[PDB]
Image 1 (cartoon, rainbow, N blue to C red):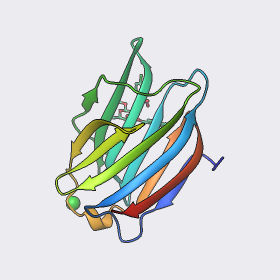
Image 2 (image 1 turned 180 degrees about the horizontal axis):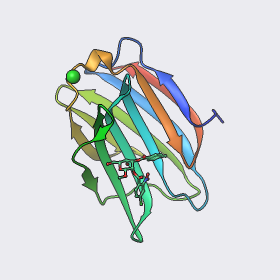
Image 3 (image 1 turned 180 degrees about the vertical axis):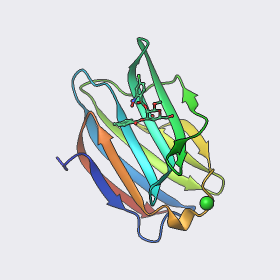
Image 4 (image 1 turned 90 degrees about the vertical axis):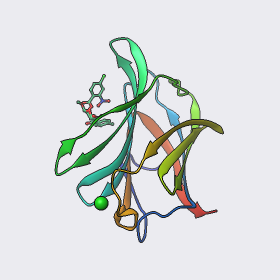
Length: 138
Ligand SMILES: CO[C@@H]1O[C@H](CO)[C@H](O)[C@H](OC(=O)c2ccc(C)cc2)[C@@H]1OC(=O)c1ccc(Cl)cc1[N+](=O)[O-]
Ligand SMILES: [Cl-]
């Protein structure tokens, strides 16, 4: 497996039609996972499965600007399971990131950070064994 936390450079940032694919396996007894699409120190798109928030499983998404988290967007549909292999696909679209897990649409996150071509790294962290992280233009 790739070492977590893992940094995937996104050369020249992101652009519509860029598809980012993450393959990994959730650890046993997982607590949290994060994908962080970063513009320097800012986080344009934080995608955070939480396995135990008040004994509920939720995906939290947010943006971090000048070290401040903004308004969370929450999705109760929770396709991850401890111990199991997953595929996360993040397709950049003109006005949002579109996320599918295990080939099923999960959520979209509208662009708050406008300079897409400066969102130049993806950080992958938390309670996974990371198998691969890659991108392709579709
Ligand atoms: C207020 O809390 C913060 O909320 C932000 C979103 O608004 C981020 O989600 C932060 O995430 C991390 O810092 C972060 C996320 C994932 C990794 C692997 C590493 C770091 C942090 O979340 C928690 O501290 C948090 C609060 C309550 C619960 Cl139950 C779980 C989390 N969490 O997953 O971090
Ligand atoms: Cl911006």
